[PDB]
Length: 81
Length: 373
Ligand code: HEC
Ligand code: MSS
Image (cartoon, rainbow over the protein chains, first blue to last red):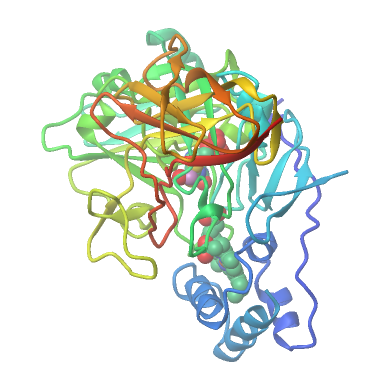
């Protein structure tokens, strides 16, 4: 038989917020990687940092995210993280 | 009972337990990225397999591998393409061994100021191991490298979750690939590679940052041009100057691929706020570089106003951690301890940290405040 490897369960979750971008981030930002990538970034980086992170995902890594959702997500992140 | 906090902002991390591993600092789960607790580096010069750090870029890592069916393909600008089993590698080629540091490009990124995006690591994204395997030079010689060859590309079993994401492929120059030190490792600390460290086979590139050390390595292509894949052309770029640095907030005007390690040193047996007995205080730690040899390690107990020469431990190889020891007289009270290494070509560590947009290559003189009583 082949050898196999068992990963533990993923538990990482995004910080809830009343902004619509929270749900848009839930729906768009966990498809390629766990959201601990977001949770662990430097804190209080602000608007330009998170705008750039979101644009990189879409333009460089081809995340299927529309313009409206992209703004919502980047705004939710900049306010929350 | 299951978290730590690294000494930079937003430093909380779970302690997580993976098969074959002791608890490690969980950075990301998918893909798994795991940092080594700093205390491990005081436990011995060779990092145990169960403690060794883990970094990946893409969620689609292999989780089932039949070692019998596994093949390493050698192709492109060669006379004879090869399909090699692990048994072929172990039996048909002589073996080589090297004790060598693997260190992430962004090891220590969390300490960079201003903070930059990416893997927020403390200093535990490095480790030292006795690697055993086949020199790449030997396998390429068997294939027969063709004149006009310029680079070799390296790809593994992992893959993007969404096919449009650039697959993880790296490149070395042909002269580098055939130098005899670049190794196709099938063994780590006398055992088959741990799964997350690239079972059953990985590239080892002594003295070079870890991005080149492709894991689960199954595809080697000799090419007659410069490779322009995303992870060479766009990612892993450093400022094209001596300090590999820019003014904080400024983009470099020209870049090149990241390459050899710069010189680093750490004191391992004390951490911030540790208590020591005033008098002769024993200090120990490690130093390493890109393979030129550590010439000296100097130690200071007065924040760099004066230096004492440490005694270097017997070496394990030019690519290994080099141990050192020093006994310093400490007066009662606070002391800022530092160590600073230099190598045989005159490379050293800066007293003040430099910066670059990606937060690669940090090697500032490490300071540690202790209390003598
Ligand atoms: C696949 C198309 C992705 C989608 C969907 C999202 N991201 Fe992503 N992200 C992707 C990759 C291949 C990587 C690098 C992984 C590595 O270990 O190198 C990342 C990384 C991040 C990071 C880390 C910082 C950085 O490298 O820029 C962050 C903060 C991040 N991703 C955030 C993020 C958000 C907000 C997303 C929704 C718009 C999102 N990611 C989606 C690929 C993909
Ligand atoms: N295949 C593969 N390989 C690979 C990868 C991925 O992702 N994939 N990563 C890198 C990196 S990035 Mo930075 O530069 S560091 C690093 C390394 C690590 O190793 P370990 O995990 O074994 O420790 O690996 C290397 N290799």
